[PDB]
Amino acid sequence: FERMENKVLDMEATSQAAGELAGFGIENQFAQLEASSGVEDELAALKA
Amino acid sequence: DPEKVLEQAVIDMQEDLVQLRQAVARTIAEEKRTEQRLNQDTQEAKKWEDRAKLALTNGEENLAREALARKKSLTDTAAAYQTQLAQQRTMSENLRRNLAALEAKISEAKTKKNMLQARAKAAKANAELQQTLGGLGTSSATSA
Amino acid sequence: EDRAKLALTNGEENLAREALARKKSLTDTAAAYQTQLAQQRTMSENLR
Amino acid sequence: EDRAKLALTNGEENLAREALARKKSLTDTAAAYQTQLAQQRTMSENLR
């Protein structure tokens, strides 16, 4: 059970190593997706 | 020659960026581990507090004091690990900014050196063309 | 767009926004292909 | 610049400044390449 916990800790360390590099402009890309969603909502409101 | 020297520098930078990425990954793993440790310790403290409550049920004031001692040890360890996590976070941010700066330096140096070399080669080729235009030797037929 | 209208019928505003996203992708692709067709027409006239 | 506008949409003033930095780098490179192109054109005319 201890050995299984060490493996989990290794997984968490890998997750941290990915997070330190996870910083991407996709976050700014997600703003465009939200803007498109708002545009579609506005179009739906126009339909009403 | 400068071409080879700067080319080797670019290659070495290609390795250095990977090394810094590995260091960042190691720091991420360390911070994750310390976070997990402090997070589980906080729960162990609550478990010992529950044992203290069980003691409060009847009699074992000694058990309550023992649980309090466990709580003190656990909270001290949690504070120490929180300080360690703060240090790891500061180091991670430092390394991240250093990596950004190093990547900028590498990219700018490589591209600027490449374009400079290309333009110097073009300029020397043009100068050679002008020399050849001025270096025409067909006038030697004046001897014949 | 017709699927979006079906969504407008009742409820699935999410379906409407999804259809809007499909519309945006399709119209962008159509504009790109129109530009490509203009290039092909210019090349065809040049070759002729 | 369009990414900067997306940032202007909401919040990420930092993204806007980053996009401005990218714009500055790109325009400086464009000016340098324009100067290089002028040199190449002069050399081409001389050789012609």
Image (cartoon, coloured by chain):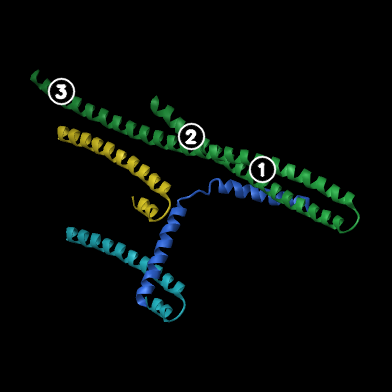
Chain colours: A blue, B green, C cyan, D yellow
Q: Earlier in the sequence, mark 2 or mark 1?
A: 2
Q: Chain of mark 1?
A: B
Q: Is residue B138 left or right of residue B77?
A: left
| Horizontal and vertical percent position of residue B75 | 74, 45
Identify the residue at horizontal 36%, vertical 66% (top origin). Answer: C24
Q: Earlier in the sequence, mark 3 or mark 2?
A: 2
- Residue type indicated by callout 3: Gly
Question: Between tags 3 and 2, which lies in front?
Answer: 2
Identify the residue at horizontal 21%, vertical 36% (top origin). Answer: D38
| Horizontal and vertical percent position of residue C34 | 27, 64
The residue where tag 2 is placed is: B13
- When the figure is inspected, residue B127 is found, relative to residue D31, above or below; the finding is above
Farthest right residue in view: B59
Mark 3–mark 2 Cα distance, whole angstroms, equals 49 Å
The residue where tag 1 is placed is: B82
Q: Is residue D19 left or right of residue B49?
A: left
Q: Is residue B102 left or right of residue D27?
A: right
Disc 2 packing (10 Å; few <14; some 14–19; many ≥20): some
| Horizontal and vertical percent position of residue B70 | 81, 46
| A32 vs A21, nearest the viewer | A32
Secondary structure, mark 1, is: helix
The residue where tag 3 is placed is: B137
Q: Is residue A42 left or right of residue B52?
A: left
Marks counted in the figure total 3
Secondary structure, mark 3, is: loop
